[PDB]
Amino acid sequence: MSYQNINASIIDKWAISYEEYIKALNGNWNVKLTPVKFVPHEWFEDLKGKKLLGLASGGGQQIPVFTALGAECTVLDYSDKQLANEKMVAEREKYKVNIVKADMTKPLPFEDESFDIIFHPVSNCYIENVELVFKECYRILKKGGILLCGLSTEINYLVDENEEKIVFSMPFNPLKNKEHREFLEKFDGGYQFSHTLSEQLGGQLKAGFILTNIEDDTNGVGRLHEMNISTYIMTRAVK
Amino acid sequence: MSYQNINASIIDKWAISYEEYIKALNGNWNVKLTPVKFVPHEWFEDLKGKKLLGLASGGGQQIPVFTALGAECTVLDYSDKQLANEKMVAEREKYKVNIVKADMTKPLPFEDESFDIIFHPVSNCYIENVELVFKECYRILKKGGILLCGLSTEINYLVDENEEKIVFSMPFNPLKNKEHREFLEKFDGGYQFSHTLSEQLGGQLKAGFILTNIEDDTNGVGRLHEMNISTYIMTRAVK
Image (cartoon, rainbow over all chains, first blue to last red; front, top):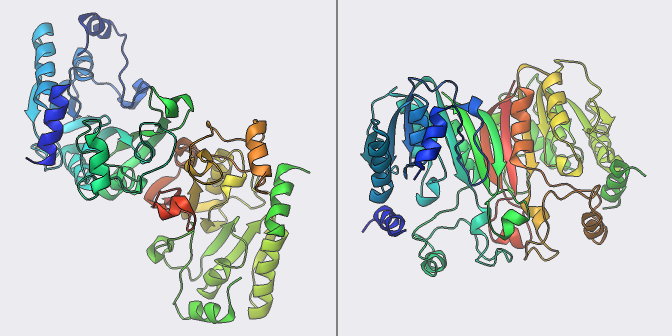
């Protein structure tokens, strides 16, 4: 089994309400790239008629909202259950959505200049190398297209469950380090990877993107969140 | 008795050799924005003939190298001892340099569009508000000019005296929190401040800079360095 298939099966082992979809149709909406903050509405521009890709954004959480606002949406995920939740909500609200099962560690199955916007919430913590994913995002966006990302860092991988003593040496890589794989095994964590700023932000620059907004967020729950420690990045970039 | 004067006296209380300067005249050189890594030479373009500002870059370690390579340099720093090092090298090599004592938290004493490049190594951990400094950098750079920075983050300000446990809630601000001021006063650390990515990177975007390169670095010594934990950013941006 590939580590990506192991991750999907763990996610499968573990959706927007009808009322919330109704609110979105009435103009009342908010989505997240990271655990706490809502994405400023201006980052998306006008979505009516825009082609949107939810990159590892399944579960029937954000795509139903973008669909209610008029976007023609495609959702890519490697978890069958995340994809099933997207289909369940599409059926409940009688809307069309292009559901694609695919591993984002590999080339994306779309043509060049196919999308106006890519919505990529926290998810690349499940893949080892992110630079190739950002180059693919650049290829499939049209000129002037928008990439919005939620991005993990190193801090959450420095600590153990006590969220206090710094115990792990970086990078956190369970493919390469027995100690990191063993820690995840105590909590059924699968294969998760720390990533540096050279990866999460420099990877977008190397692909050609112009970064326009960079903001911080916290975990939403737990000790590091209560201490107001910034553990995630929210980014907007344009091609 | 201001915090900037306190920091300057602590740094004072705490330069390149002739051989190293001559190596630099011969195109054999390396400088740092952060504790460990050398700055890629391509980030500067060709220094010959460029007007360069070392912003809080005193100590006689980088400015003599850029002068050897043909840049016309100004060095700004608030530590008398750091500026003395620049004076000792300039007199030994008999080159021209503009040596300016000034507090970079306040407006910089330069005309708009005056410099081709600003070199800004790790230093803004000693000041509370960094967004105003980036705006001043944008004002004094020529169109098409380059800003190179070494930037501190939050991790170094999370930890106890042994770099073991995460004990401080953010932001770390000794002007506002007695507990933070007391911690530094135990190590003769002065007044240092944590800064977020919204500040260190978003502050460059809000001033008008276009980020072109983002890399990470470590502390160079101590427990977090031995664990390879990234605690600094290296950046290049263009106006």
